[PDB]
Length: 281
Image (tube, rainbow, N blue to C red; front, side, top):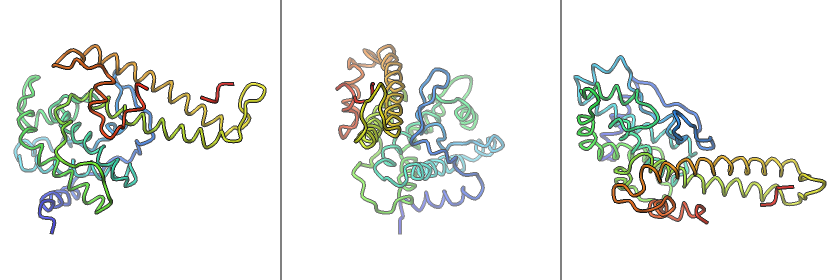
């Protein structure tokens, strides 16, 4: 029947029995974490890629088993994302792309959350000293199959629900992780800021400012949630814009400033709320 996905579904079922399962953490409404001065996407925290240290030698001797472990991990990563987004297809599709590229970053050892998974992969692929060429070669050879494994994980996860976004090999694959994370941050900010603003609109209907603060407590709670989110996000935006301006802007033929980079990379008007009210009493 599904002859493209049979290879991946079969690798997935055979590996599922031996190894463990994903970490359920429901990252969707979580705040971004600062780890070693770096803002980390909530999605990245429990990305499904765990090398069992007692298996390093087997993966070193059997390249087919290592290829299979990566395809199974990428497939399972999609399943984890489907659970997190409650089957909202358009959200899973977009997040799959970021997870796929972070899988690439972890393999290549350019991941900014941790070096432990990357370290072990370096041993498996035989990389030496601090060199990453062996892992770069493996990524460029297997990345198209890895995306197919993820597309298959997606297909198992949602059979036919309508999804607007394209599913071709992600153009973001060549983009440095900081920039991908900044885009994810930006899209996530506009979406959540809207939802929190709707909650503020929904609870502050009959609410009025009398003798200082607002009368309705459910409205005050939505006001503080909104204000705390904006204060936090304004700071997260400055830290990211500062790193953008200092390390990326005017380098590698990129004369664009942060909002223009986002205007170019965010598709479907997702970052428009960037570069563009009744609680304070």
